[PDB]
Length: 308
Image (cartoon, rainbow, N blue to C red; front, side, top):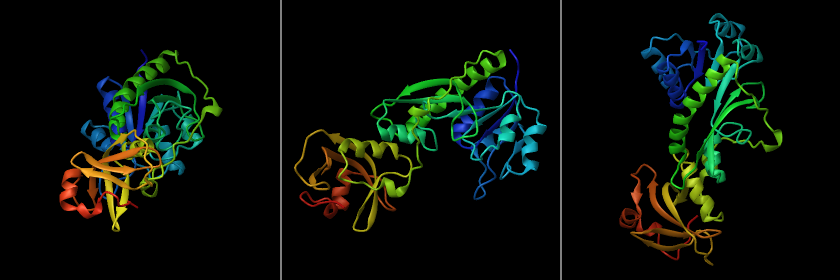
């Protein structure tokens, strides 16, 4: 029942979904910190804070004591950090009364780090979720105050999981804020041994490696959607893969061998099983179905030929 003065720090839409939830549930958000304007585009959090008449602060860094003081001045009870791109110095961590609380996109201690959502999908996890944690100095080492899980379906991409977590996160956050205001929060220490780090995604890593199993390639295709998107090079042309299905049939064909190319898809042998490419997007072109591809890029997918 204690109305907490909250400083909200966040940047992307995922973060904006959480701010919107805090406001909508009558929370006392005293200030909003977002990353400085980007080439010059304002963040989804900045846009929403503004529309709501909230003071926005965009220090390029919290290292300067001048910037740290902006947090001090707001005399906050807790600082909620959701996808805010700046490192918080221990000094700032100690400033709000109840400290800083972070909404992390994984079921900690698994997937500490930068790309928890994409990595849980890529790794083949059966589920993800969000962990609301009491921020500490390391990279996502804080005690877990709350966790909500969400299963990862076979049709999920990092994009849909983001959607799912953007809906789960706010409720977990509001619940946790209630517990902190009530003194009923039950902090759980992270088991170091269960930790894994969700390293950033790169376009280099998204390039299709046919020697992998069709299952993992199919997972990469989903996990790397919307960014960086799995891709292969054909005639020095980067081609993004939007959809593929796995054909659980063993092949003696070398990885990369096109086994079939028709309306049903372009089947490619992998290191284990067959990957059926369904939607590909040649650079600077539209995302085309296998049939469209056979009409405009036939020579790229001749059965018997080997990709890559």
